[PDB]
Image: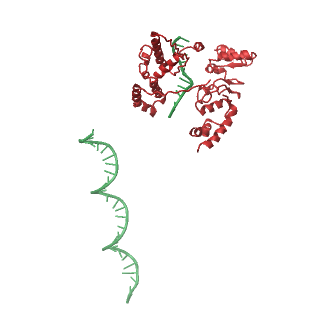
Amino acid sequence: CPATVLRQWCNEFHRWWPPLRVVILHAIGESRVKELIDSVFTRGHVIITTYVGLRIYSKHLLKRDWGYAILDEGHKIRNPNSDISLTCKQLRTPNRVILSGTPIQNNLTELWSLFDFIFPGRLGTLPVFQNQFAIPINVGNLQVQVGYKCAVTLKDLISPYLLRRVPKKSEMVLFCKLTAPQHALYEKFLRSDELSRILQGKRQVLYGIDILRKICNHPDLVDVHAKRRSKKDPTYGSASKSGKMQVVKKLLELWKSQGHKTLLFTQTRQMLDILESFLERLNAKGAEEEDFVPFKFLRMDGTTSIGVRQSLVDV
DNA sequence: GTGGCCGTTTTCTGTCTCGTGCCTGGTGTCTTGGGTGTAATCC
């Protein structure tokens, strides 16, 4: 189980079934873990492990036989060929159960790799799994019917191996335009040597679409002095240059006076600096004048500690 | 509140030489004939 539910997983054991003994894979539940191993198979009933902690004591875990196997992680297995398979699929037990309602999110290769852990391959090998129906599903008449049967065969083959069970919502998508300073920086980066250099193969496209998203968030994020002016230059953020501040200012102020607890969502902690300078400036403007209320934001990320979590989640 | 590592998202005329290949002058090895030689047999 993840490290965010470690105590939780021991808790239901304690409350529902006290007769079941339990031992987490930590300093308690290099010799000390070996005395822990002493009578962890006869006396010990259930062993708990964080899915980072197996490769801390795997020397004396993967060796002996095991019974029932539970893994509460269906998005940290995904596709094959990773440390996942290295420390997981070497377990010695038919009983293999995964607890996750989102196993399929990227591709059917993840499906094959997840089916491998539970069953020894009722479908076939990875080359077999691919050559069977990988391309036909993607491309697809000339595809549908043969593809229809080749897919329903898979559905009947794996269906008795994974269970499936399922106010209102408004999805308004606004299509804003690139500003003129944005279009200039877009064309400048558009016609440059680095893009072709990435395309031919010396680099990866992952570093050329991260920088063209770096300009869409706002112009001032493709600067070389990003860290040098992120939190010590009160002009780094700015407004109306991003092409989205106006549909941010208007949309957030339509709820600020309306009193609607709203969620602002990003992906980068670097753009958090800009949206945080922006909202501090909004706070300054509101506080200087009257008939208003402080914006009162907060930012949470991996920089903070695991202890904080729920607290802010609650506040 | 310090970091470790994995996990992740996409598809230079200029001149010379060194070597050799080709042409040629020599030279081997031979073939024909021509006379010398013997045969020889008419009568």
Question: Which quarter shows the N terminus of chain A?
Answer: top right
Please report the residue visible at 58 percent of the width from the left and 27 percent of the height from the top. Answer: A82
On the question of residue A12 being in view, the answer is: yes
Q: Is residue A167 left or right of residue A206?
A: right
Please tell me which residue lies in front, A292 or A42. A292
Q: Where is residue A166 in the image (x, y as percent from the top left)?
A: 66, 28
Q: Camera-side residue: A191 or A216?
A: A216
Tell me which corner region of the image, top left, top right, bottom left or bottom right, holds residue A260.
Answer: top right
Q: Position of residue A97 (x, y in %)?
A: 68, 26
Say whether residue A122 is visible: no
Residue displayed at 65% across by 23% down: A72
| Residue at x 66% of width, y 15% of height | A7
| Colour-to-chain, red | A
Q: In this view, does B19 lie to the left or right of A201?
A: left
Shown in green, the chain is B
- Residue A47 point in image, percent of width and height: 69, 19
Which residue is nearer to you in this view: A193 or A180? A180
Q: Based on the displayed image, in which of its 4 quarters is residue A94 positioned?
A: top right
Residue occupying the point 71% across, 19% down: A46
